Amino acid sequence: EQRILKFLEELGEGKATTAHDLSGKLGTPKKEISRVLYSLAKKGKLQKEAGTPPLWKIAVSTQ
């Protein structure tokens, strides 16, 4: 919970991302990115796009 909030914050406040792009860049297992993503978005510590592909973007997106 300290390695994900340190990389997602450096991304670029206002930049969306995917789960496959995080499990393939850091090597982390999807089972670890799917169980943590649904645990952060529920606490309001990560926005959630609307559609098929669940994109994440640190609170407060561009514009």
Image (cartoon, rainbow, N blue to C red):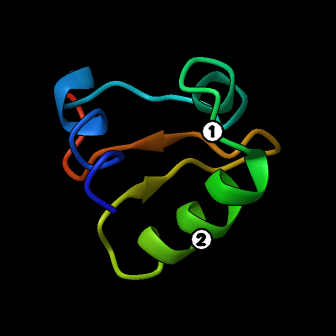
Marks 1 and 2 sit apart, C-alpha to C-alpha, by 16 Å
Count every numbered label the image shows and give the total.
2
| Picture layout, residue 47 above or below residue 11 | below
Question: Image check: 57 left or right of 7?
Answer: right
Q: Position of residue 4 (x, y in %)?
A: 36, 46
Label ID, residue 28: 1
Q: Position of residue 53 (x, y in %)?
A: 76, 39
Residue assigned mark 2: 38
- Is label 2 in a helix, a strand or a loop? helix
Q: Residue at x 32, y 74 (%)?
A: 44
Location of residue 58 (image quadrant): top left
How far from the left and from the top, in percent, is residue 54? 68, 46
Relative to 53, does residue 47 appear above or below in the rendering? Answer: below
Question: Against 44, is 62 above or below?
Answer: above
What's the residue type where badge 2 is placed?
Tyr
Amino acid type, mark 1: Thr
Depth order, front residue of 60/35: 35
The disc, 1 or 2, on the residue closer to the chain's N-terminal end is 1
Residue 15 in the image: state x and y as whole percent.
Answer: 34, 24
